Image 1 (cartoon, protein in one colour):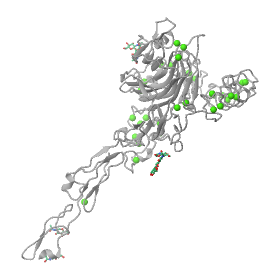
Image 2 (tube, protein in one colour):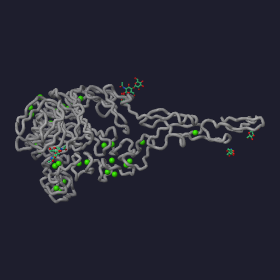
Image 3 (cartoon, helix red, strand yellow):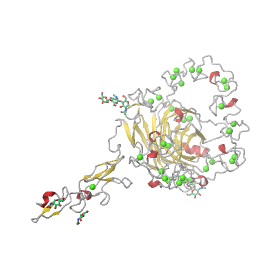
Length: 621
Ligand SMILES: *[C@@H]1O[C@H](CO)[C@@H](O[C@@H]2O[C@H](CO)[C@@H](O[C@@H]3O[C@H](CO)[C@@H](O)[C@H](O)[C@@H]3O)[C@H](O)[C@H]2NC(C)=O)[C@H](O)[C@H]1NC(C)=O
Ligand SMILES: *[C@@H]1O[C@H](CO)[C@@H](O[C@@H]2O[C@H](CO)[C@@H](O)[C@H](O)[C@H]2NC(C)=O)[C@H](O)[C@H]1NC(C)=O
Ligand SMILES: *[C@@H]1O[C@H](CO)[C@@H](O)[C@H](O)[C@H]1NC(C)=O
Ligand SMILES: *[C@@H]1O[C@H](CO)[C@@H](O)[C@H](O)[C@H]1NC(C)=O
Ligand SMILES: [Ca+2]
Ligand SMILES: [Ca+2]
Ligand SMILES: [Ca+2]
Ligand SMILES: [Ca+2]
Ligand SMILES: [Ca+2]
Ligand SMILES: [Ca+2]
Ligand SMILES: [Ca+2]
Ligand SMILES: [Ca+2]
Ligand SMILES: [Ca+2]
Ligand SMILES: [Ca+2]
Ligand SMILES: [Ca+2]
Ligand SMILES: [Ca+2]
Ligand SMILES: [Ca+2]
Ligand SMILES: [Ca+2]
Ligand SMILES: [Ca+2]
Ligand SMILES: [Ca+2]
Ligand SMILES: [Ca+2]
Ligand SMILES: [Ca+2]
Ligand SMILES: [Ca+2]
Ligand SMILES: [Ca+2]
Ligand SMILES: [Ca+2]
Ligand SMILES: [Ca+2]
Ligand SMILES: [Ca+2]
Ligand SMILES: [Ca+2]
Ligand SMILES: [Ca+2]
Ligand SMILES: [Ca+2]
Ligand SMILES: [Ca+2]
Ligand SMILES: [Ca+2]
Ligand SMILES: [Ca+2]
Ligand SMILES: [Ca+2]
């Protein structure tokens, strides 16, 4: 009777008595107390912890009837708890898993592509790369028979892609820059006459310029219309400031307005001419800027002149104690993104925004308020470009380092490993593909061309191809390069040969890929020379860490691909070498903590016509 007037509340059970009175029992699932005046419950705010709190405080959503778990935020995947009431709230809990299209096989990569996980917080998280022996954009992969990253045919990405889609213009000769001067679809590298003027390039004194008459005023054998110094002998055509007028006929070769002979750094632009120590070598080119040293002698090839050079480097990252922004913790790259003098490695706040490294959703970009308005766990201020060097993550070979984004050996140090007086045959390095391909031309002394970028953890690969039948000697590459007495080297001999100098020690150089760590008590010279050639250990010189026991030599005119994995933090090293698509050498895991990082470089020891093509390095920290 009494319940007929609905004095209670929608859903709430009204109990009616014989005398007309009533009482209100339940409040319907998900509501407050008092059966008469009833209100909505917050299952979220003050009960359990139903939803997946992505390093934050939000996430669970309270509705007027019931409650709501947000869908798993980007980079994650799970279920989405929906509940009517309160006993449904302690039971049922949101599990969100960290996504990984590589391990989850949800990727869109080609059968002959590898899905590569870029790391949880990367933009994007994964990419597609064609496997060795193939080329493309990762979605489509075709045969790449010389491993120079350009496929043998035009592929169905030849319209939508920048690189690796379009007929390799020298199908059988590594030429990762695909330079084709006359544009006749035959690349410079295999083209017989590069400028289509009828003079074959071996005879042509202006190889990349049309000049059929061959006019050569001075007999420097570099013809008129390409000679940067037409009236002055200069076969190297060196042009320091790449202005079109070569050094030979320039009174100011670096274009800095201070004339040569006045210039205290004749090769390096320095209008300001500052010379702190007064030694006549300006700071910009002074390898010992604080200490008098006009001769600039640098006997161990680390860019620190003999006079500053004390080798005291207690953490083995190759920067000495007095020149190390983290003297005690290895950090070969010396990264210091906030520029406060404390290296990323020892500094607990790398951008100086108050939010410490471990708790910062944009570790390298200033953002105290940690705005992440799409919920992807990354501050929106570093959305595609973690290190803020304006190169997006996907195109950045070192996405957590603003000093490096491109594989580039365009500028390199020549490190001569056995300098002398006449037998001095220097390596000749020619650079193509904007620093991503080097060809060594000469049957030369041991020598390295080492790039200037520095690495802790690193992956480094490159195409190895010897474009001649002559000789059977060494080529390869270095990593963790610190000084000419401190590097790891991978080198590769064709035929086993004992070195033609029995002094100072007999060196027997076996065929096969050799992984070695140089730790020389003498530095450059005959002792290290021989030790480098020798397969095995040489006390006070070289220690061989691995060498292919099958002893397989490289073949003439044959494309190989090496892949170095180096993780100095543990000491992990892995060297893979590929012939075409098939692995042909694998060191397996190696462990060596002699050097906790350093630079990369290419290596020759008495082998000419060596192509180091389609070079790539990446930071893997
Ligand atoms: C990069 O550009 C190429 C340009 O060809 C893309 O390849 C093409 O991708 C489309 C998908 O957008 C395929 O179209 C499909 O065709 C059928 C009809 O045959 C249509 O019914 C489907 O709805 C679908 O759109 C197309 O077949 C494919 N071309 C081939 C044959 O390879 C490529 O997809 C682009 N990269 C990406 C993001 O996938
Ligand atoms: C490379 O070898 C050098 C010398 O062969 C090592 O330096 C010596 O280290 C030992 C400790 O085992 C000391 O007793 C010597 O005094 C050191 N020699 C000198 C004069 O420096 C060095 O440890 C090795 N480099 C590494 C592992 O980084
Ligand atoms: C009907 O509901 C009204 C509330 O407006 C209440 O005053 C009345 O007591 C109810 N009828 C009964 C129980 O006799
Ligand atoms: C229920 O809440 C209302 C709020 O106005 C109040 O008037 C009523 O007295 C409450 N019931 C109880 C416990 O007496
Ligand atoms: Ca509610
Ligand atoms: Ca190719
Ligand atoms: Ca080619
Ligand atoms: Ca051509
Ligand atoms: Ca040519
Ligand atoms: Ca031509
Ligand atoms: Ca020509
Ligand atoms: Ca010519
Ligand atoms: Ca000339
Ligand atoms: Ca000249
Ligand atoms: Ca010039
Ligand atoms: Ca000058
Ligand atoms: Ca200068
Ligand atoms: Ca000086
Ligand atoms: Ca000096
Ligand atoms: Ca030095
Ligand atoms: Ca040194
Ligand atoms: Ca150090
Ligand atoms: Ca350090
Ligand atoms: Ca710092
Ligand atoms: Ca730090
Ligand atoms: Ca700091
Ligand atoms: Ca910070
Ligand atoms: Ca930040
Ligand atoms: Ca974000
Ligand atoms: Ca970047
Ligand atoms: Ca970078
Ligand atoms: Ca040969
Ligand atoms: Ca030989
Ligand atoms: Ca030789």
